[PDB]
Each structure stands twice: as C-alpha cells, then as structure tokens.
Image (cartoon, rainbow, N blue to C red; front, side):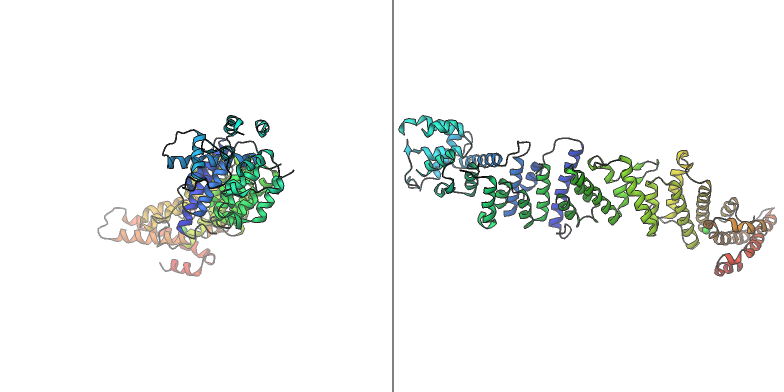
Length: 569
Ligand SMILES: [Cl-]
C-alpha cells in the first residue's frame, strides 16, 4: 500500500488521519471521544460491499464500548438489537408507521416471512391460535432479546397447550425454543428450518454456549469453515465470536488502511499493534512526518513498559531517517524560546521518564550526526534547540566567513527570495539579534566568537554598500573595522587573526582599493568644486599606498589570482 499512489486513496488517508488526530487530542485532554462513532460517520456515506461490511463492524465495536467485557453476552445483545432494528425498517416500509409496539412489529414480520402469499403457511406443522404461530412468535421475541414479552405470550396461551415453569426461571419453532432454553441436544447444534440468515446462526450458537459447548468450540467451527461459508458476513462473524486478531488479518486482505484503523479501535477497547502502526507509516512517513507522529503516538495506547520503548524507538527512527527537524523537534523564535515541534506537543502521551531529557537527548544526538555528515544548516538548527549557544556562533562564523570569501563582489549577498533559514547573512543576523541582545544567552558565548560574528556582520553590511556603489560610506565602515591600515604592525598581526577573518581580508583590500579608485575619479571631475579637493585625493592615496605595502607583506597568504587583480588597480 502507498497512500500517495492516487488521489482516491490519498483522500481516505487524510480523512482517517484527522480522526486519529482528534483521538490523540481526547486522550491528551483526558476527555470524551467515540472513535467508532467517527468512522461510522465517515463510512455511512461510503459505498460498496466492503464498505457496507466495514460500517457494520464499526457498529459492532461501537455497541461494545464501556460495557462489561463478555464476548458471548455482547454478541447476543448485538444480534438481538440488530434484528429488532431490522424488523423496524420492515414495518416502516410495509405499514409505513414507526410507532407500533415491539410485539406488533414482530408479528408483522412473522406474518410476511411465514406466508407464501397464498395466505398459506410456508412451514407445515405450526401450532396456531387466532391465526398466529405462538412458537414462531415466542422464538422471534427471544431472537429480539424480548424475554419479558416472550414469557407473556407463553403465559397467555398456557391452556391451549411445564416448559413454562423452566422458562420463567430463564413444531419446528417449538423445537428451537426448547432447545435454546433447555440448552439440550447439543450434539445437534443446527435446526435449519427456522434459521433464515447468518445472523440467526451466530445468535443460535451464542445462545447455546457453556452438555458442554464453549466459545473456543464456537470459534473452532467458524475458523474451520472459513470465509468461504460466510459470504459477506465473515468480518462481523470474526468480531462477534471475538476472533479479533483474525478480524484484522481478514480486513488486511481487502484494505490495509481499514485494517490499521479497526486495530486502533479494538486497541482503544483493550482487546503487533506497534508493528501495525509502524508499517502503515512507511508510505506517508516522508511526505507527512506530522501524520506519522500521530499514528506512532497511538502505540502507547497500551501502557506496558515494553511498547512505550517501541514508541520512542519508532520516533527516534522517524527523526533520524526523515530529518524533518523543524517540524518534529521544533524551532527557536525571536524571543529565544523554543517553539515546540509535533513530538513535544504529544509528550504527555509519550510516557517519558524525564520531560526535559527525552527531546534533549534525541536533539543532541541528531546534532553530532549532522556535523559529522557535513549538514551545516541542520547542525546550526539542532545546536540551537540544544541551547548550545557558543557552538552555534562558531558554526555560523564558519558558514558566513565561507559565503563572503566565496561569493563574487559583483553579486548581491542577499536576494528577494532569500530567508534566515537558507541565507548565511540572514541567518547570522537572526542569531545575533536573538542571542547578543539577550544577556542570559550572550554570557554563554565566548566574547571572541561574539566579536568575530559582529565583524562578519559588519563586513556583510560593507559588502551591500559596495555593491550599490556607495564608495565613501563603504570606506568609513571599512575603516571602523580596525583590520586594514588606514601597516607593518597589522601585517605582523595578520598571523594572529582568527582563521575566519583572514580569508576575508583579500576581498576587503579589493573593496577598499576599488572604492578609493572610484572616489578619486569623482574628485577629479571638473564639476567637482571643493576647496579641500586636493587634501582628500592625497588622503585617499595614502590609504591605498599603505594597503599596498600591507598587501605585499601578506601576498602569499591569498591566492595569486586575487593579489594580481588587486595590484592591477
Ligand atoms: Cl568580503
């Protein structure tokens, strides 16, 4: 199965996921939720053989919630209720009413199912009174769960006739009633003339159970005959007999998705689950990591210490293999506070040993994995969530330093599409503004790292000035850097510069020298009237001259290629 194979299957996935979503919400708010009711709602509008079969299975589960656990009593209750409802629909069709007594809905039923049209009884040897078959009536009252009424009918006709003595304690139809009430002749479980449907058969057996006829015996018979002999009522049969594992199996044969969700239903009723959910996750795990988390969180539906470990393990393998860190593990907001990911939202349901250490451990681990894989952006994101502030600055300083030295001066550092997640300049600005102005966080950062970062930000500002041809403002910003000789002293210090700064100096010199060439040209124009024209030129030529000697002393510590474009300027 693959939930993304087509749009017909994809929609069903979304509808079911929303249900599971609301279920986790109830579990967590410790509130009221009726999952069976939910699917019943979604399936009642569906159409087909299997869908009609699934809709009824959910009704079976629904009619079973919050009830004393008793497979046989619950199967009887269900089948009896269902027959009653069935006789209702028949009355509301034949007599078009809806307000007749139970007893009358049933005589109306008995009357239209035991006559050949001929006003001739279809089954010979019926004991009759006032034109109505007392044992047939008595049987279908039982069959409807209406023991009070069945007893009344027996009492009334007492005389036209002490099985009645035993009945109070507890023709073919007369044979059935004695057999069911007496629970006699168990060797002959079947009395077919009065069995007109599969529902009737299952109910007959359930009646008979625990001279000795056990549920396990009933189940054996069912399994023995297999799906072959239950037409389109095998799932119901499986659930009614309490063969829950086999019900799921069977549902897998025509619909993996419905099987998963039926299993969620039985589980929520407390009756390979982790594996059922982990497997169903496989196809939408990468395209919908939030839905994956929702289904895996169901694993703790059972509170055993064993399957809580299965849940954490599955969640670990989700984050490691999908690397949807932001969604799963969260992200840091501009106030410095973590904005929870999906796993942190469902943490109550996770039954963790330590609220804070569970996510921290996964995060720290994924972090060491990211910097070993060379995933720089992942690393930065993860070390933020780890609150490893200093490592974050170090990694940003490298990333930003590398972007500056490797980009061309002619090309803008930052486009209109760029964001703090993908652009090193934008990213670094975001980190500075979240961490440097936050005293609690800044103290955790090494003053030198913070220095380098500010420098790299200043340099990125200088770069945008330079690109927009703001020569003079570039120069005065360049001068505040305290890096270039506005000489010999600083070339000697060149060896003590941070490794991140030194790869930026060659471009700094090319910007500096090129702003000077441009200003000088502007100052030489005729239109340029200033009384200090000449002292400005000279002063610019001084800076250029000192950068040149500086440049020459450090010439083999930048590519010849750049030292050459710098000399020829
Ligand atoms: Cl640069």
